[PDB]
Image 1 (spheres, protein in one colour):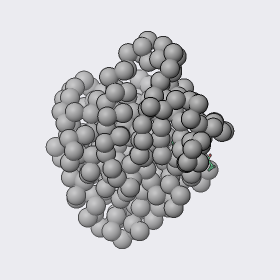
Image 2: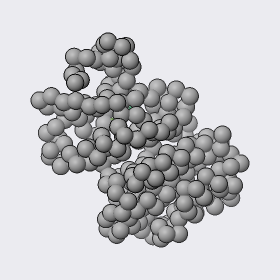
Image 3: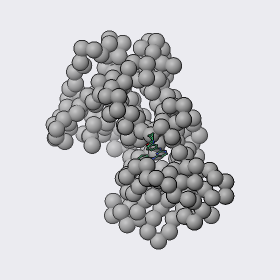
Image 4: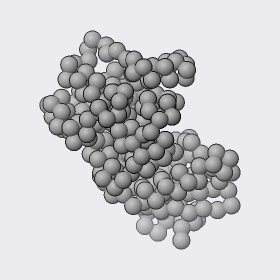
Length: 256
Ligand SMILES: O=C(Nc1cccc(Nc2nccc(Nc3cccc(C(F)(F)F)c3)n2)c1)C1CC1
């Protein structure tokens, strides 16, 4: 039975959705971890307790080198506390704005690691549906880790905009092919420095996503163009399997 008294709190890592994440050390063992603090009142108001419950259930039970481990949880009067694996090298989000854009080797490596992780998730009937750079963390060896499971629905079939597929914004039926779409958007954003449907406006981004209207800058190689164009199909059925993505020649040539 964990309590706040069991941990020494350190620097704030991030300022989060429903509260900050802190660096923490467990007192007995000196184990370094991340403490995600969520405010109950704000969870009530947003009405996302189910998604939190699913998140907790999913992340505690899944075991993958490219998925951030969840060790446990506890609460008090005002807060819920998530006890998380600490990822030393931060978010791919910060990494992206620091480097501006990624080279093909770094990108294909990240895509490989994500595809492996999502392939595992999909085999356990878990669909992420909230994949984006700020939910992607880097471990001590720079290995990509899915940070959490977001505030999405995770069932095999269900019904910023930048990372959501056309079937999800149009209120249509959506499945595991959502994560393939997200993989296409990430691959584009990694190479270009911005997501393919980015706009100054929500209403415009919505239009871009629905029309699937994006263009490549000249420096995007044909192998990269081929994978991305395969992933960003309007019709989910047309999107490749994660298995095909892992075998794609551009991935093979460039991934570590
Ligand atoms: O800042 C550094 N590293 C760093 C920044 C931010 C986060 C981490 N690690 C980490 N490990 C486990 C979990 C998290 N979670 C987390 C990190 C950042 C933001 C949020 C959000 F937005 F959900 F609150 C959650 N972060 C590590 C240091 C320069 C390299």
